[PDB]
Structures are given as structure tokens and as C-alpha cells.
Length: 279
Ligand SMILES: [Ca+2]
Ligand SMILES: [Ca+2]
Image (tube, rainbow, N blue to C red; front, side, top):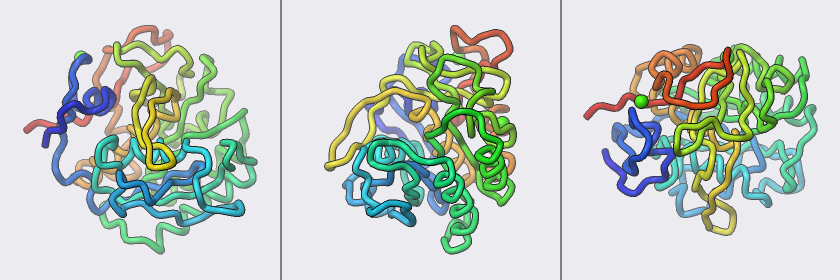
């Protein structure tokens, strides 16, 4: 399938080269998979989600996304126009308040929630969790992410936006999950992207158009934007049967575009998420 005039990041994930504008993907499109977006929520009524999004948990007075960040990330995972996996099921877990902040204790509860809640859902092609969040190093946050992954969920987490080594941030620094850095449309490391040995992969993160609250759209930047490209890619590849929740991060690294990115510090992988879709 071909989506013309797609956001650059979608075009990039199905291309060997920068500078194109059409996204190519297998029409299965992540059908039968599920992606949990652990964030500020998801505006499920947005026409872009086509009834495929729902809120499943909140730790606050509402499950509404009063911020936009979670809705944007969910859009990159699975919206019809802005998403990688256009037929996946999206589940919102609101661990971040409407200012975009959340206590680590709440974030941990949210991860444990997903590990159990997947047993309440129909995801025959597998389960992914996208975590566009984080703060300073915490062994408890890392351990929660490790548990979620161990439980059979493909966990993708943001590397962070500190232009620093991700070793000092969580859940970025948890080795067993998929830690995602950000690139721009010219195949440069995004200016803010963290780096380091713990990164598994890069995805598009600068100037990413997606859904926003109030039935709108907007372009924003962050490792938060790169992460859902990888989460959606995992869901897509799992629906195709090419990989599994336990092996998807490795598979994505195996099949990535190699050596395309600039300003990657010595010791950080030069790997850009790629669907290897061949019609
Ligand atoms: Ca290339
Ligand atoms: Ca890893």
C-alpha cells in the first residue's frame, strides 16, 4: 500500500533514503495487534483513530487527554493518516497529568497495569507498549519496564531529550527494553536526542505531524515522537509474523538502515528504523 504526501517520518521508515514523501506498507497494517500508549491519555473520539482507540486506565480525575502529548504519540502509532500501524488497536493509560508530568510511583503502577491488562484484551498478533516519558535514573522504574517486557510486551521507550548519555535516565537506561533516539528529515541526530550504548535504534523525531486534542493536528519534536514510530513498527511487524514481542527490538535493529545518520557519537548505534517493505 502507498500513502502519498505522508508525514516525512512515515516515508522515512519505509525508505532506504531520506527525501521522499510516500509511505509504503503492507495492508495488514498491524491488524490484530495492540499498542498501549502510556502517557497523558488519548482523545479517542478523534476521527483519525476511527474507533480503534480507547482509554483503559487513568490515575487522575479524568481519562481525558487535557494536554495533547499522548494523543500525538498515539497518532504516530496508529492514526489513519499519521500512523505507522493504521489498523492496530490503541489503548490509553493516563499516567501523566494534563501538564505532562507524573510521579514515578504512578508510572510504575501503569506499567504493571499493562502487563496484567493485556490478559483482558484481544491481541492475537501481540502487544506493544509505547513510553514517551522519563526522568532521572531509577532502578524501580527500570525494573517495572523490565517486568513489562518480560511479561510478553514489546516495550519501546524514549531515550530522552537531554543531548546526553541515556545511561542517566529512566526507563531509557533499562537494557531489556527498546530505547529509541530521534533523527531529523535530513538524517541528522536530532539536536536534543540522547545517545549512548543503551540506545537500540533511532526513529523520526524532529518536526513530526500527528493528531492533537480538540480534533486537531500539529507538528512537535522529541524522542517522544521517535518512540511511537518504533512501537507502531513493532506492532506492524508482529502482525506480519516476522518477529515477536520478545525479539522485535533486536529484529528492528537487525533490519534497520545502517550508517545513514550524522552526528552519531562514537559508541552509539547508527541504526534507523525501517520496515523493509517490498511490494
Ligand atoms: Ca540509506
Ligand atoms: Ca535495549
